[PDB]
Length: 150
Ligand SMILES: C[C@@H]1CC(C)(C)C[C@H]1NCc1cc[nH]n1
Image 1 (cartoon, rainbow, N blue to C red):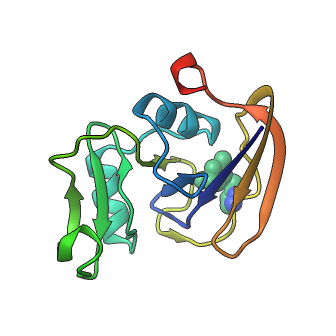
Image 2: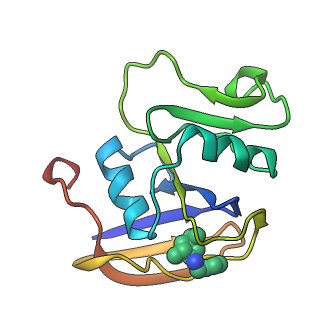
Protein backbone atom coordinates (compact mmCIF):
# COMPACT_ATOMS: atom_id res chain seq x y z
CA UNK A 1 0.00 0.00 0.00
CA UNK A 2 2.31 2.73 -1.32
CA UNK A 3 1.94 5.94 -3.35
CA UNK A 4 4.90 7.89 -4.77
CA UNK A 5 4.25 11.60 -5.55
CA UNK A 6 6.99 13.27 -7.61
CA UNK A 7 6.79 17.06 -7.18
CA UNK A 8 8.52 20.04 -8.83
CA UNK A 9 9.73 23.54 -8.02
CA UNK A 10 6.93 26.03 -7.43
CA UNK A 11 6.53 29.03 -9.76
CA UNK A 12 4.23 31.73 -8.40
CA UNK A 13 2.80 28.94 -6.20
CA UNK A 14 2.10 26.48 -9.06
CA UNK A 15 3.72 23.04 -9.11
CA UNK A 16 3.38 19.67 -10.83
CA UNK A 17 2.59 16.34 -9.15
CA UNK A 18 3.00 12.95 -10.89
CA UNK A 19 1.66 9.83 -9.15
CA UNK A 20 3.53 6.52 -9.34
CA UNK A 21 5.57 7.56 -12.35
CA UNK A 22 2.65 7.24 -14.77
CA UNK A 23 -0.40 9.27 -15.93
CA UNK A 24 -2.70 7.96 -13.17
CA UNK A 25 -4.74 10.70 -11.56
CA UNK A 26 -8.44 11.32 -12.24
CA UNK A 27 -9.93 14.85 -11.99
CA UNK A 28 -11.53 14.02 -8.59
CA UNK A 29 -8.26 12.54 -7.26
CA UNK A 30 -6.38 15.62 -8.49
CA UNK A 31 -8.54 17.95 -6.39
CA UNK A 32 -8.01 15.72 -3.32
CA UNK A 33 -4.28 15.51 -3.93
CA UNK A 34 -3.90 19.31 -4.19
CA UNK A 35 -6.00 19.68 -0.98
CA UNK A 36 -3.49 17.36 0.78
CA UNK A 37 -0.77 19.93 -0.11
CA UNK A 38 -3.04 22.77 1.26
CA UNK A 39 -3.44 23.73 -2.39
CA UNK A 40 -6.05 24.00 -5.14
CA UNK A 41 -6.15 23.18 -8.87
CA UNK A 42 -4.68 26.30 -10.55
CA UNK A 43 -6.86 28.61 -12.59
CA UNK A 44 -5.72 29.28 -16.16
CA UNK A 45 -4.62 32.82 -15.03
CA UNK A 46 -2.54 31.35 -12.16
CA UNK A 47 -0.91 28.90 -14.61
CA UNK A 48 -0.16 31.70 -17.12
CA UNK A 49 1.58 33.72 -14.40
CA UNK A 50 3.61 30.64 -13.30
CA UNK A 51 4.64 30.12 -16.95
CA UNK A 52 5.80 33.75 -17.13
CA UNK A 53 8.09 33.13 -14.10
CA UNK A 54 9.80 30.09 -15.64
CA UNK A 55 7.46 27.10 -15.24
CA UNK A 56 7.41 24.44 -17.91
CA UNK A 57 6.92 20.66 -17.96
CA UNK A 58 6.63 17.92 -20.55
CA UNK A 59 3.51 16.31 -18.99
CA UNK A 60 -0.20 16.70 -19.27
CA UNK A 61 -1.82 17.71 -16.00
CA UNK A 62 -5.12 19.04 -14.71
CA UNK A 63 -5.75 22.64 -13.92
CA UNK A 64 -9.27 23.95 -13.11
CA UNK A 65 -11.27 23.31 -16.24
CA UNK A 66 -8.63 21.86 -18.58
CA UNK A 67 -5.68 19.48 -19.01
CA UNK A 68 -2.55 21.44 -20.02
CA UNK A 69 1.21 21.48 -20.53
CA UNK A 70 3.02 24.80 -19.77
CA UNK A 71 5.78 25.35 -22.37
CA UNK A 72 8.44 27.99 -22.59
CA UNK A 73 10.94 26.42 -25.04
CA UNK A 74 9.65 24.67 -28.19
CA UNK A 75 10.32 20.93 -28.09
CA UNK A 76 8.95 18.50 -30.68
CA UNK A 77 8.19 15.83 -28.07
CA UNK A 78 6.43 18.16 -25.55
CA UNK A 79 3.09 19.64 -26.72
CA UNK A 80 4.25 19.25 -30.37
CA UNK A 81 6.59 22.32 -30.40
CA UNK A 82 3.96 24.69 -28.97
CA UNK A 83 4.77 27.44 -26.46
CA UNK A 84 2.45 28.95 -23.87
CA UNK A 85 -0.11 27.05 -21.85
CA UNK A 86 -0.91 24.22 -24.31
CA UNK A 87 -4.44 22.92 -23.84
CA UNK A 88 -5.23 19.28 -24.59
CA UNK A 89 -8.25 19.26 -26.92
CA UNK A 90 -8.88 15.63 -27.95
CA UNK A 91 -8.20 12.52 -25.90
CA UNK A 92 -9.98 9.24 -25.34
CA UNK A 93 -8.73 8.92 -21.72
CA UNK A 94 -9.29 10.50 -18.35
CA UNK A 95 -6.08 10.10 -16.22
CA UNK A 96 -3.23 12.54 -16.23
CA UNK A 97 -0.82 14.16 -13.76
CA UNK A 98 -1.99 17.31 -11.85
CA UNK A 99 -0.93 20.83 -11.23
CA UNK A 100 -1.55 22.42 -7.81
CA UNK A 101 -1.43 26.01 -6.59
CA UNK A 102 -0.42 27.08 -3.07
CA UNK A 103 -1.15 30.75 -2.37
CA UNK A 104 1.36 30.94 0.51
CA UNK A 105 4.36 29.94 -1.65
CA UNK A 106 6.90 32.52 -2.88
CA UNK A 107 5.88 34.87 -5.73
CA UNK A 108 8.46 33.69 -8.23
CA UNK A 109 10.66 30.58 -8.57
CA UNK A 110 10.92 28.38 -5.52
CA UNK A 111 13.18 25.44 -6.25
CA UNK A 112 13.54 24.29 -2.65
CA UNK A 113 12.40 20.76 -1.88
CA UNK A 114 9.02 19.75 -0.45
CA UNK A 115 9.33 17.97 2.91
CA UNK A 116 5.65 17.25 3.85
CA UNK A 117 2.00 16.50 2.72
CA UNK A 118 0.63 18.71 5.50
CA UNK A 119 -3.08 18.14 5.04
CA UNK A 120 -3.07 14.37 4.52
CA UNK A 121 -5.65 12.43 6.52
CA UNK A 122 -5.19 9.46 8.81
CA UNK A 123 -4.89 6.28 6.78
CA UNK A 124 -2.95 3.16 5.92
CA UNK A 125 -1.03 4.13 2.77
CA UNK A 126 2.70 4.87 2.80
CA UNK A 127 2.88 8.14 0.85
CA UNK A 128 6.28 9.28 -0.31
CA UNK A 129 6.99 12.76 -1.62
CA UNK A 130 9.86 12.56 -4.08
CA UNK A 131 11.68 15.70 -5.16
CA UNK A 132 13.54 16.13 -8.45
CA UNK A 133 16.82 16.11 -6.47
CA UNK A 134 15.81 12.72 -5.03
CA UNK A 135 15.13 13.89 -1.49
CA UNK A 136 12.20 12.12 0.06
CA UNK A 137 9.67 12.43 2.92
CA UNK A 138 7.41 9.43 3.75
CA UNK A 139 4.35 9.32 5.98
CA UNK A 140 1.39 7.05 6.60
CA UNK A 141 -1.93 8.51 5.47
CA UNK A 142 -4.64 8.95 2.89
CA UNK A 143 -5.92 11.83 0.75
CA UNK A 144 -8.67 10.32 -1.49
CA UNK A 145 -12.29 11.16 -0.63
CA UNK A 146 -13.96 9.41 -3.65
CA UNK A 147 -14.21 5.56 -3.61
CA UNK A 148 -13.90 5.15 -7.42
CA UNK A 149 -10.29 6.45 -7.06
CA UNK A 150 -9.28 3.73 -4.48
C1 LIG B 1 2.23 23.34 2.18
C2 LIG B 1 3.06 23.78 0.99
C3 LIG B 1 2.87 22.99 -0.12
C4 LIG B 1 4.20 23.28 -1.06
C5 LIG B 1 3.94 24.49 -1.95
C6 LIG B 1 4.47 22.06 -1.95
C7 LIG B 1 5.24 23.54 -0.17
C8 LIG B 1 4.61 23.70 1.30
N1 LIG B 1 5.12 24.87 2.05
C9 LIG B 1 6.30 24.57 2.86
C10 LIG B 1 7.56 24.42 1.99
C11 LIG B 1 8.23 25.42 1.30
C12 LIG B 1 9.26 24.82 0.60
N2 LIG B 1 9.21 23.54 0.85
N3 LIG B 1 8.18 23.27 1.71
